[PDB]
Image: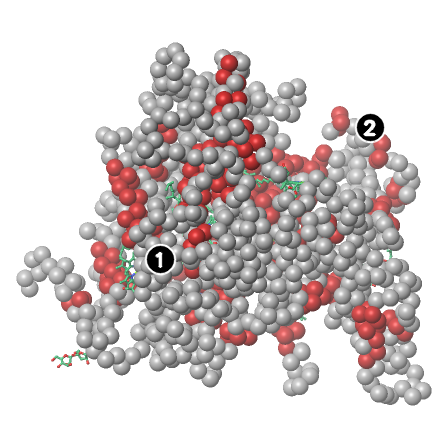
Amino acid sequence: MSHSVKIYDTCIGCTQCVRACPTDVLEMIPWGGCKAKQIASAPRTEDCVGCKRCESACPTDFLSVRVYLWHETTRSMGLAY
Amino acid sequence: DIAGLTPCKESKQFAKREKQALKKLQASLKLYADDSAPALAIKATMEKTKKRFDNYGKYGLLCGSDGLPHLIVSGDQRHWGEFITPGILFLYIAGWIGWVGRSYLIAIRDEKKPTQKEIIIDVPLASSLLFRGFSWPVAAYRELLNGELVDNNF
Amino acid sequence: MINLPSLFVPLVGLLFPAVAMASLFLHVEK
Amino acid sequence: ALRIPRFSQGIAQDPTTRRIWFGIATAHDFESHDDITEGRLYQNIFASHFGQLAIIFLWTSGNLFHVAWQGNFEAWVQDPFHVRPIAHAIWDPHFGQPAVEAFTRGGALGPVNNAYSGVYQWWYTIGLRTNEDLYTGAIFLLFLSFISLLAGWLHLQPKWKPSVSWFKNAESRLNHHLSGLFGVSSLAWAGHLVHVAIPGSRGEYVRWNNFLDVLPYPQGLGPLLTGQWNLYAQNPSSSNHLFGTTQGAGTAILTILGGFHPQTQSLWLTDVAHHHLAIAFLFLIGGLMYRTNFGIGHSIKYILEAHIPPGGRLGRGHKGLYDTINNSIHFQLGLALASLGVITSLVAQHMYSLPAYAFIAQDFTTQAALYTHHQYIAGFIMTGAFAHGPIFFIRDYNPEQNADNVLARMLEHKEAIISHLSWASLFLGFHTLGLYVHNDVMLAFGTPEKQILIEPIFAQWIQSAHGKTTYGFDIPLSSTNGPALNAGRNIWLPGWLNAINENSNSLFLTIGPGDFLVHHAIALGLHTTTLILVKGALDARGSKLMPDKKDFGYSFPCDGPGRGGTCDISAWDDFYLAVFWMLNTIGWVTFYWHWKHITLWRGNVSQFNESSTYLMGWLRDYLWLNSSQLINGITPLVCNSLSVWAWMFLFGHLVWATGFMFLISWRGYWQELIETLAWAHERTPLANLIRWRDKPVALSIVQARLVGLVHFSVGYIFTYAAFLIASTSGKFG
Amino acid sequence: PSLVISLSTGLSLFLGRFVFFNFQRENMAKQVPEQNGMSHFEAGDTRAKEYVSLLKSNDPVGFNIVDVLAWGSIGHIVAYYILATASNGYDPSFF
Amino acid sequence: FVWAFSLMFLFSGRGYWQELIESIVWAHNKLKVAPATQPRALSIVQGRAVGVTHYLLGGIATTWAFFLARIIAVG
Amino acid sequence: TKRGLLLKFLILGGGSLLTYVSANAPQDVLP
Ligand code: CLA
Ligand code: CLA
Ligand code: CLA
Ligand code: CLA
Ligand SMILES: CC(=CC=C/C(C)=C/C=C/C=C(C)/C=C/C=C(C)/C=C/C1=C(C)CCCC1(C)C)/C=C/C1=C(C)CCCC1(C)C
Ligand SMILES: CC(=CC=C/C(C)=C/C=C/C=C(C)\C=C\C=C(C)\C=C\C1=C(C)CCCC1(C)C)/C=C/C1=C(C)CCCC1(C)C
Ligand SMILES: CC1=C(C/C=C(\C)CCC[C@H](C)CCC[C@@H](C)CCCC(C)C)C(=O)c2ccccc2C1=O
Ligand SMILES: CC1=C(C/C=C(\C)CCC[C@H](C)CCC[C@@H](C)CCCC(C)C)C(=O)c2ccccc2C1=O
Ligand SMILES: OC[C@H]1O[C@](CO)(O[C@H]2O[C@H](CO)[C@@H](O)[C@H](O)[C@H]2O)[C@@H](O)[C@@H]1O
Ligand code: SF4
Ligand code: SF4
């Protein structure tokens, strides 16, 4: 919000867990203690489109994201062209 | 007796139905079976819907206009077992479908890995928990509401 | 003159539309 | 890449076309979109629907204005024999010379289309008559419907307050309304029918001049204030009447006496007025029930609070239901919707068997395209009712502020609620459907007997304890006498509520096994319709698959694939999904009346009898019988009687069908070939440089669930529209 | 048959229970408390209610019924008139 | 009829009949009668599989009937 | 080619005379 879908979980470990999703998610930002110690929910999200490939894999244990962003550029949908 | 008319003992409209309609059945002056041994309108199909004469049994059975028979079942004058007689029957049969539903089920979730024993079937129909149903005298009508499925488990 | 009351279907069902399909192309721009 | 749409902002600089559509459908969503404050909002719905009342009088004006110079009236008030009234003059340059053929209808000159709205039997039925005497309508209503806008502005202008907090009282208002409004709104009507109208009905005229000189009697309001009322009701009307011209008139307003007549059915002259009067105490007695400063009456909490009937010692709270129905504005607009919804049909199911108009049923058309625009709507409401009470739960609502509290618990103990609802349907499902195939496997098979067919006992029952003095029958204490009433008799139930069987217009039609099904299949509708609305609502909040389904609740249609696979699981898309059964009940029900009526007019009734107890037949004779008239109306042999209708009726079948795209298409496939189809232009001469200002895209992933719908619907609702008319008009009936 | 004036007798039984307090203490409306202008804020909202104030004339102006309702109803309303009748007046017993 | 049952398979969401399938699954557990073999709604595209296939075996035999009934008997 | 503020002029004018007389007529030759 403008890209606000929560995939968070609690492990935020990313080995045999989740990577998939065009650019958007440059994480591994180890918070001072959470097991395989890499955490949060995103990096700078003003770049790419609206997947839920975002979970599909590696837990969000609650929801999982999808489209919810509304304010929606174009670069933010393939088609501005 | 009630809203429609009276039973079979008299029902004019009903009579006319017997008669034209079926019997036209007839309708085929011949159509060849002078002695021949197949084409069976001839014998019954009529006579099995037909020898069903001024008798069908006698059943009361109310019969409105056009004299197709209507079902009251309010437990009176004659009509009681057009719902209850075949009603408790529907109850008793089901419930001994699912008394055993809640049975070749509550017999598994235990021992060692019990995770789909059910896509095959352990005792077919249950053939063990089987009669538990006719072997319901009273049964769930007490032991459902007291103990086992007990409010606890509620 | 005789028999002539036909203007309140184009000024409406025709010309009023012209206005707004033009005009309201204010949604695009003004 | 500029900036535009003046309220939203995310929408405002979106380079595609969404820019547009989504503009024209966020407009009315005040609560939370850029421009808003709880002060703004309220008022921004207040001088909105002052923009209401306003548009309702430019409707009504013109209703009374395509009528006064053409569109027979100094006709149809000479005697209204069932031949083709008039709305307005149809004028399309596309018309052939068969302008001359009916379409062009008798009395008037150029072609026209006749009142199927009632108006024509109530601008008449409260007197209002003479064609020199008549040509007001707009003139007033409009010298009204402009004032309707004036407050709009006046009360929009800051200064002479538009009022902000003052919008959450109640007590004061509704302590005001259900007196000030309704009560006196009645009364004042009671006023009018009686001084100017009842005289205009049985008796004679009222001349625009005198209003003092006219006096229903010789010696005035006589006693009246003299508690002596009674001797209104003696020789009031008669029956050897000749409606509108006295002679067997008599003149003593009020009654409950006399009743039906082959010359007009319709509620008696008076009764619709002592009533209008009579209720007008109760609401005035009701109004004055709550505070409003002086210091009597009531505070609208403290009689909820710990009021509670079965609460008390059953551990189940009642906290500020007031500051949540009040702080909600959606709870508001959906206790509003329903009541209206439940009563929109009570209106429109009572408006038959008790129509209150001078020639209506015994018209039998206007009477059948008027029960339904009040059945459509009404169904159409209900949904919206159920749909703003699944928005309360998301935008408003407040778990910490409502809890142990009986609006909660309703949430909390919810899984059951949909189940003991769904258990109704599934039962009401296959059990109606055994009875109706069985009833159709048995015919076809040769055996009309064997047919399963239950009398509708508890139905007719209600009525042999009324007036359905059908072919005798005691009933233990009743018999058809010994005890009758004893405590009641020659007062009250006189000739009225005594229509009996009356094969013509008896009020109650004499019910059998045909009606013990539709009547269980209107019951499988509002049940199924509502397991989905109840459900739709009972968690716009969230659930297992989508737990945290919120901050936006309503229309977030779609979600990512995975989890189980997730879809139309916004409380909107269940509303979306709901509206199909509100369009399937509100069809079984309407469908039913008519077949019935149809047959119960220019002919039989045995017809619906043994031929509605099954299914095929519902399609064959009705559906297939009774369309006849219309379709061979474009006929290879020139445009005959109706043409508007049948072309509508196929316009009906297209708008419908063309729903489906929207509905089996799903933005993905559309957008992508528009990706190839917007490589054209760019790559083709005599169509280059030429820039769009909105980027070619395919419809939003909620939008098209709507549009297929808002499409499925007109088609559908524009098909029965033209179906019934196009066949209740011909007839035969 | 009907006591018609059985009950209009009856209803302004009660709204004279109305003729009340325009008279007796202080001003109108226990003076506009809260009406225009708008409550504290209040706010949930809000007050007041009081199971404890259904007295004050329970006893006194429960007579008000029998007023008009006696001698001024079935017994020919004020026979004791005269007080300027000539552009007309009377008035005259419909009873 | 079968055709006019397809639309329900064709026209609808999916975590819907889930959201529903649980209310069900709930009432199920109270009597102790459900969980084993995690009951689940239709596999997004299965759902489309049970559109289509029905929409056809509906919308088709409709005429297979419509036909044999207007060549048998006059014609 | 004096286009310096116009078009509103040619859309009352031109289009009140492709429709004023264009619909009216002195003796039908009807629909
Ligand atoms: C969505 C649609 C909508 C539409 C388009 C219509 C259209 C219609 N309805 Mg209707 N209706 C609707 C929703 C709608 N209704 C709903 C939701 C309800 C349930 C509440 C009804 C209940 C209803 C009834 C009961 C009837 C109609 C009737 C009608 C028809 C009469 C024309 C008319 O309404 O003029 C409307 C007229 C006005 C708006 C002006 C009159 C209003 C009066 C009461 C104002 C009083 C204010 C007064 C000045 C205060 C005086 C104070 C002082 C002088 C003392 C028309 C076909 C009538 C009919 O049967 O036709 C055959 C009638 O039967 N409707
Ligand atoms: C009687 C009144 C009532 C009132 C006062 C409101 C008020 C409101 N509704 Mg609402 N609603 C109602 C009845 C009402 N509703 C009913 C009966 C239903 C269904 C039965 C709905 C279903 C509904 C939905 C889904 C939503 C609202 C929303 C809203 C809010 C924004 C309005 C909006 O989005 O319009 C803007 C719409 C337009 C400017 C026009 C586009 C509308 C399309 C669909 C046209 C509809 C069919 C049309 C007549 C066919 C074309 C005509 C044809 C002849 C060419 C506003 C609070 C929105 C909301 O805020 O909820 C969170 C939204 O979600 N309503
Ligand atoms: C004519 C239609 C078709 C049928 C048969 C159904 C049936 C049903 N819909 Mg449905 N629906 C349809 C079209 C249909 N829908 C369409 C077009 C839409 C909108 C696009 C919807 C939108 C909708 C919603 C929102 C809901 C339903 C629900 C339901 C169920 C409600 C419970 C009930 O009515 O009794 C049960 C069912 C019947 C009477 C139908 C017959 C089912 C049995 C008898 C099958 C026959 C067995 C047969 C002998 C074996 C053949 C199978 C094979 C071995 C050959 C029911 C299964 C609701 C629900 O889920 O209820 C819990 C609710 O979710 N529908
Ligand atoms: C009755 C139908 C409705 C209509 C009109 C269409 C039309 C179309 N579909 Mg389609 N479709 C529908 C229902 C409909 N569909 C449904 C129900 C489904 C699935 C359930 C689909 C699944 C589908 C698919 C997969 C595809 C299409 C495609 C198409 C396009 C094919 C090219 C074409 O000939 O279009 C133009 C011609 C028409 C739409 C018919 C003529 C319309 C008439 C009434 C003339 C009106 C014009 C006139 C100027 C009106 C202006 C007057 C003013 C008052 C507005 C076309 C837009 C395809 C496509 O885009 O390929 C090109 C694509 O393959 N459809
Ligand atoms: C009075 C009555 C009734 C009824 C019934 C009823 C009384 C009904 C009701 C109904 C209602 C409804 C049906 C409503 C609904 C709605 C809802 C349920 C809502 C919901 C919601 C949601 C969704 C959430 C939140 C919000 C809201 C709340 C909105 C009756 C009476 C009678 C009778 C008949 C018999 C005889 C006698 C008499 C007396 C004559
Ligand atoms: C209700 C029902 C049924 C219905 C049904 C219906 C209502 C319908 C159905 C249908 C089916 C179908 C339909 C199938 C099939 C088929 C076929 C065989 C086909 C063929 C073909 C081909 C070859 C191809 C195409 C064309 C055609 C189609 C011809 C039933 C119910 C029930 C009950 C009560 C309970 C128990 C069970 C039962 C007994 C079951
Ligand atoms: C055809 C189609 C499209 C393509 C989008 C199209 C075809 C838009 C084409 C524009 C039409 C031709 C406009 C004609 C409408 C007029 C009535 C004018 C509208 C006026 C408004 C302001 C009301 C989708 O994007 C889509 C998305 C999701 C599910 C289904 C579908 C779908 O079926
Ligand atoms: C109605 C509907 C459902 C609900 C449909 C369901 C749950 C159908 C599956 C029901 C099964 C087939 C019943 C099976 C139970 C019996 C086989 C068990 C008893 C064995 C026999 C002896 C009876 C979806 O899951 C769905 C998914 C995606 C898009 C659209 C839809 C959709 O429209
Ligand atoms: O009413 C339509 C009728 O009028 C027209 C329109 O041009 O023109 C008439 O006006 C001229 C002017 O002198 C007359 O001489 C003659 O009536 C027509 O030219 C004519 O087309 C239409 O027939
Ligand atoms: S839950 Fe997803 S991405 Fe989140 S922390 Fe784990 S894998 Fe990282
Ligand atoms: S889930 Fe969202 S953020 Fe993640 S990759 Fe997909 S689009 Fe990008």
Callout 1 secondary element: loop
Question: Given contact means CB atoms under 8 Å apart, are the residues at marks 2 and 1 in contact?
Answer: no
Quadrant that contains the N terminus of chain E? top right
Whether residue B82 is visible here, answered yes or no, is yes
User: What kind of residue is marked 1?
Assistant: Leu
Residue furthest right in the image: B35
- Say how many tags the image has: 2
> Can the viewer see residue D580 in this picture?
no
Q: Identify the residue position indicated by label 1 in the image.
A: D64
Name the residue: 35% across, 38% down: D45
| A29 on left or right of D35 | right
Q: Residue furthest left?
A: G2
Q: Amino acid at mark 2?
A: Asn
Please determine whether, in this image, residue E53 is positioned above or below residue D370: above
* Residue where numbered disc 2 is placed: B146
Category of crowding for the residue at label 2, using alpha-carbon neighbours closer than 10 angstroms: few (below 14), some (14–19), many (at least 20): few
Pointer 1 local density, CA inside 10 Å: few below 14, some 14–19, many at least 20: many
Counting from the top left corner in percent of width and height, residue D443 is at 75, 69
| x and y, in percent, of residue D659 in the image | 47, 60
Judged left or right of residue B137, residue D28 is left
Residue at the spot 61% in from the left edge and 60% down from the top edge:
D505
